[PDB]
Amino acid sequence: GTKLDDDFKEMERKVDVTSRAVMEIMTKTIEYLAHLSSLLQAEALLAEAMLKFGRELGDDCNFGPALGEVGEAMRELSEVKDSLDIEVKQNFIDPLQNLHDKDLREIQHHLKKLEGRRLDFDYKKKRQGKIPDEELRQALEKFDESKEIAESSMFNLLEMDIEQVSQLSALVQAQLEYHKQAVQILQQVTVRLEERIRQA
Amino acid sequence: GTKLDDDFKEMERKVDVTSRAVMEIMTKTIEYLAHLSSLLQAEALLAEAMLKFGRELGDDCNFGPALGEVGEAMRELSEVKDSLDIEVKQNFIDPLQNLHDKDLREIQHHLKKLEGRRLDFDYKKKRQGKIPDEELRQALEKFDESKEIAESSMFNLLEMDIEQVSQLSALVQAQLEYHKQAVQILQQVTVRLEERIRQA
Image (cartoon, rainbow over all chains, first blue to last red):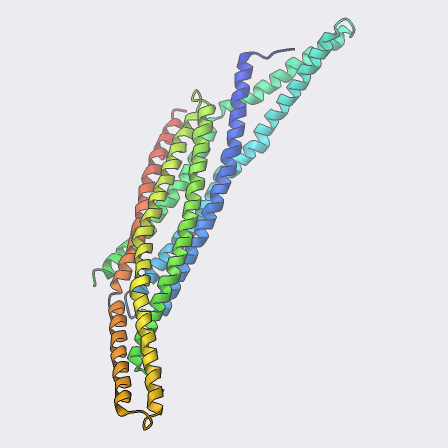
């Protein structure tokens, strides 16, 4: 039947990939944040157990207040991990989700409508003499018209891809913010333990 | 029956706590490393999925090579997390495990032997005239002797607690090493994305 130019085709492939990537990347980033939460929880637990025994054991010794120093340090890291979840979630996931329920969905729609209009024209073309020229003409009009709409929505999404890179950036952003935030917490308690071991 | 001085008692309590702490702390640190591995895995997956779609999508655009830049960055972080597991495991867990199968176990043993010898003396004391003085004397000798052995092993463990603090330090060590190691990886790719978004 009717065939679409290669440009249109390549443009479609890219949109496809993009759409599928945004799909998996998003699901796996969610699975990722699941385990992050899981670890974050376990962290806080270990942290408490420390703050706890460091209590019971008493502070007249060394291991007692140390379990307390490392204790809170561990728990603060824990809370920073939670902040990270929230960051990734609303600055990377949500945007991609919105891209999928808005732009990608709409493209998919136009593409379906284009296919329908294409098939319908190929059919009405088969019966050229049988059907009134006006009807055929419209069939062709509708096809061209749908092709144009699909080309625009696809093109606009593909041309705005620098924003996907901003989103990837957003992820790496919150990522770096957490690790830097943590290097502080740790580096701090890493000096307090340096003391004790020195007041040895 | 026979009672042990308060110093001996307090010394016993501390040893108890310490022993129990080293127990939970260790189990929870293991549960912690479990989830760390779990997240680490999920990270690498997301990382691959990126390196993948960034491939398929192609590099003639922006999102393609970006998914590749953030792609490996994510995977390298993943591998650093694995290094961290190994660190915590052999520089914090293993030491504590050895403390539990060596020093703590031995104390527990001495303590049991002390109890036996105590109970046995209280019994042989009940039957003072009934049993030969020599036997009673030995019973007392054995008790004092076991008490001394228990006091030494407990005291030595409690006096060497600065080493627990070194271990806590070891944990916080590997912890800080990972986060600093990561701040690099990220900070790096955080500048490469700065470029693309600038060559916009």
